[PDB]
Image (tube, rainbow over all chains, first blue to last red; front, side, top):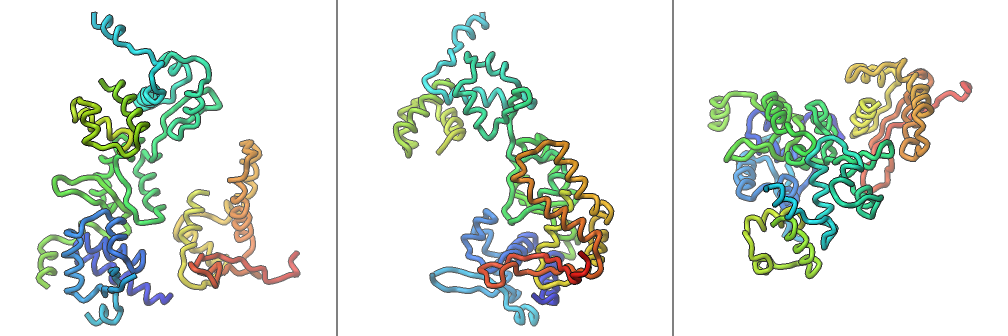
Length: 88
Length: 160
Length: 44
Length: 111
């Protein structure tokens, strides 16, 4: 893909690394290393609880970073809108 | 008198099930870090020739049969006993699944220790409990400094 | 009584695969902490 | 050889099409790790002598390293009239992109 898009990915990475908690770092690194995620698959991969998942997802809503997706196959998915993240 | 009681209570290894004999053999293999020969087995259980027990022991994954001398040894899941091997394993991670520390304690008896000094070195991505700082599922430190910037600066970015 | 009850529970999973924990109680009638440690070593 | 496979694995996971020189590959090799051109030439002879001494006649797991030694001695001898091509699509029409490094012979007069 675009090397500038790779620079954007490393930029978001460094922003969370140097300016947010380690759980936020691990969540964003997991969703960049992989792609869009169901919550159950992420909970398997990290072996965590929804109580711990809650405030992280809420603060990532608050900074307008993660674009959630909701569709039935209801199944919860997460990605990031690039211009929303850039303008935020 | 205690030896007399132990000899009276010494059950013959011709048990109802062979799995007790197998479990005692794997316990005696596990409690010795070195490979042990066939004569240790033949002294341990009253069984002499290469039995179905010995053949299934050779077929066992945790037991290494030796074509050289017949030495049988325990096989651990993690063959890492050095931080350099641990860091190379962490670099060679193909998925982001965490790796447990109990089966690293298998093979490497001081492994949680070295995990603590490498986390002190900011060399890993640890997951720890809140009752205590616990070596658990860990990941390779692809990040920068874990202990990067101080808590007051972190708190005023939280104020931001 | 470690060694005998390991053979006895080997017979129990031979008797039925999903044997009840509550049903394991009367088949042992032993210390349950000893039983819990012995159950964790083989299966569920 | 294990850290050479580590270098090949970390250069394997590219995202787009790269067409580099053998000189550029060797320069990035010496930049990242400390693998040199003369050991990369000698690796084929070294592996052949190791297999002959070791008596490892079930070479079913071992037959793939011939490719790596072949490529290493090729790229550490040949640099001009040849190009190293690196692509993220081993199969372009695939469900998943397997990536690929490609070597190119460009002059047919050489052999």
